[PDB]
Amino acid sequence: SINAKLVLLGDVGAGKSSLVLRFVKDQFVEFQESTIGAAFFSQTLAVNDATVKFEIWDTAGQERYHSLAPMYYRGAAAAIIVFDVTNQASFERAKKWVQELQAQGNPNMVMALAGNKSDLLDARKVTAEDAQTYAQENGLFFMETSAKTATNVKEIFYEIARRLP
Amino acid sequence: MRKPSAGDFVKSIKSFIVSFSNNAPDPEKDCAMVQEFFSKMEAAFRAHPLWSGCSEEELDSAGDGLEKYVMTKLFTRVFASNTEEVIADEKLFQKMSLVQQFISPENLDIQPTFQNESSWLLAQKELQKINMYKAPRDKLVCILNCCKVINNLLLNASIASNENAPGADEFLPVLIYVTIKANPPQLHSNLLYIQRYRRESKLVGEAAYFFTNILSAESFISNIDAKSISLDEAEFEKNMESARAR
Ligand SMILES: Nc1nc2c(ncn2[C@@H]2O[C@H](COP(=O)(O)OP(N)(=O)O)[C@@H](O)[C@H]2O)c(=O)[nH]1
Image (cartoon, rainbow over all chains, first blue to last red; front, side, top):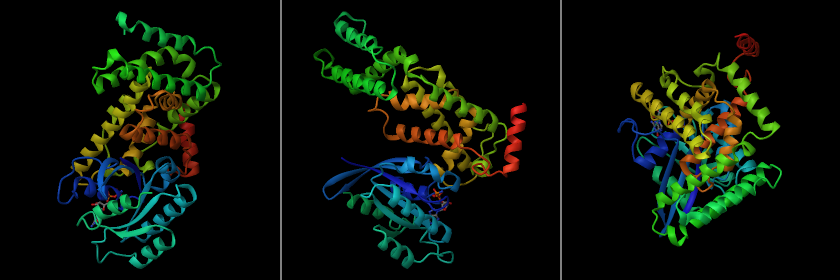
């Protein structure tokens, strides 16, 4: 009864699909086998004795499709911009999405920056500091997430639902 | 609807069709008039003292029935009905009939792990059925079937190559390929017509998501150049020439 359109932005391999499947089905490919695609989902959540229903829109992350994205994020009440903490190039890309939504998305959009694959230790290349700093400077919140271990998956969607104008 | 109780519903729908010619064709107004007529007849289905025993699904079917009847009458005045839509159609057809001859899945970032060996033939065929129907619903259903088929085929590829579930990153590039290979006639007018004339209460949810996918596919395809399908400018232009000769 609060109906939200939520877009997932970020480049291929970041973990947009893994994130939303953890959130929706509570599965990760390595533990449960694959059942359904992850491009579109409806999900309801209880927030503060109310109800918030998410329509979740995946987008193609490849460079050649970048200029298509505004058609997807048009009228989005919220966005999760995902990056892979082990890929510095994914982080750079996530900041451009933020900049773009600020030039060209809704000012009352709740953006969340998700730093995915937190569970990967010897691979990590992006600091909590930079992500956190970046998000603090640009009016959005940063969370570290993991689809595999489930860390901060439910919570990032909860925190988005909480902040809904 | 032929039953004698429905006499005055029938008169009403028909005085609408006759009263539609009374204005010079204009898409933005025309479709506004039809959506309002739909909004109003549909209000008259549920609220009607005779139709107060109907299930939600039955009232929804009657909506689609009205849509179909009305849109079939209005079809030639409202569909691809001016020069600029005709021109955009032909530009899209031209580009696809050329590009379909040399495009490969790697031009669109389709990974070998998500390859289908029919080249998603059944999804191509579902899409090409689009000009077999006149109602926006049945046109949209072709798009939606195409999408479902693509998704089931992608899921199969992921199972086989032990990959994670497909998302927009896998789906959209495959919708683009499939659309190019299908080259469905009057794709631009077909989409505009669905957008305008489909019962607006129904262009929502998953339906609207996959619709937005095909609209973004149309847009990508219109704008295909060497750089957008990752080919050298000389390789691209030379591929286009050989396509024209066939
Ligand atoms: N270790 C780890 N791997 C992940 C995580 N999230 C996604 N992955 C993996 O990284 C790959 C890309 O994920 P995917 O969700 O397909 O990316 P996309 N293209 O953004 O949807 C997949 O193999 C997936 O299993 C995570 O939190 N931890």
